[PDB]
Image (cartoon, rainbow, N blue to C red; front, side, top):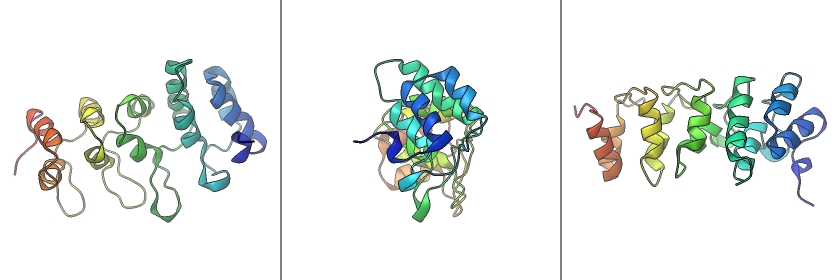
Length: 179
């Protein structure tokens, strides 16, 4: 049957079970003596495991706090996956709401962070979301609204180019430099 044992063994499996249980104090305890960043099987990581298991109407605030506590303990929210697949922070910036990114910003994720594969500001991932909530979270936490990619494009230029009007209008309302 399907269980965290699909991905993890040993001390990582013990911590994956505490994550699955939404047990914040036990996660805090186990994290110290667990390799937080070594992938398990199928490229699964403990932090991706915490993002998946947060989707539960039981103990929801505590399950978001498990994400925060894993990052404070040294789980890397910017760790890439193989073959150019993205990090937990980049992944949750495309989501329909900002609960995940807020849990990571609460653990000291920089709103100006760049990805470790390509060096792109992770805030560009918000332009892929269906609404402006993750961009609002990053700008609210003090992201540079005028940060550029390697070719000098801003969030505003990219949003205009794709006709992502809701993102354009939020960026303008927040004072994004149009030149």
